[PDB]
Amino acid sequence: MSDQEAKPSTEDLGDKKEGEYIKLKVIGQDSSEIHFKVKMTTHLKKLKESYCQRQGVPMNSLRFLFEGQRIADNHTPKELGMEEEDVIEVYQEQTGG
Image (cartoon, rainbow, N blue to C red; front, side, top):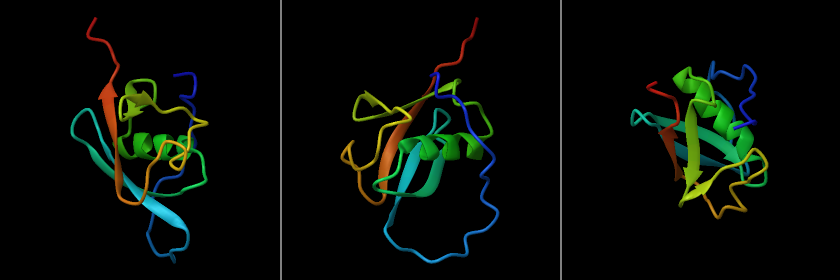
């Protein structure tokens, strides 16, 4: 939650070579399927902010979890046991009141 910070890294293009990075997909609270490419040994934080910006919503309004575990900014895909084309679950933690 406190890791609700982010920076402008919008996808302008997708012209680049691959290497050691994997792909992951997110299911948003609105069934928002976001696709992103991140390293195995990098922080999930960039992934979380990356998909949040895709939807155009703050990271504090939604919940990022996998296999029933919250994803922290210091959490990594490799440590959480993820791989290429893996999928993460996102819910809404906004408020109706």
